[PDB]
Length: 75
Image 1 (cartoon, rainbow, N blue to C red):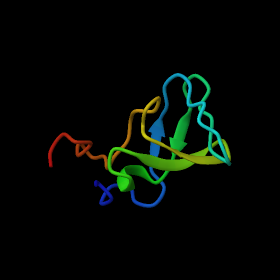
Image 2 (cartoon, rainbow, N blue to C red):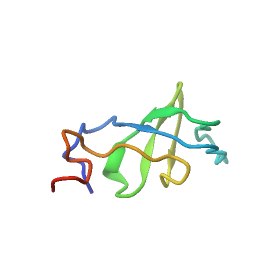
Image 3 (cartoon, rainbow, N blue to C red):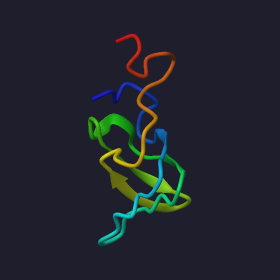
Image 4 (tube, rainbow, N blue to C red):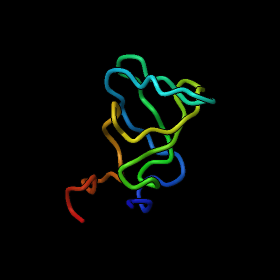
């Protein structure tokens, strides 16, 4: 639950296909950068991609979560 990070909108990079749209989610096609909610979904994020908003279980998307070598590095 690294909400202490960049807060609100935090940017993560997505891997290959976040396909997950049922109602109104984002699709991260091969390698998109998101700025979602960050760690607010602890291990999961919620955010927007190129204006397409959604949320993922960081499944296809790995990156972010409070930087300054605190991306899980020194906690």
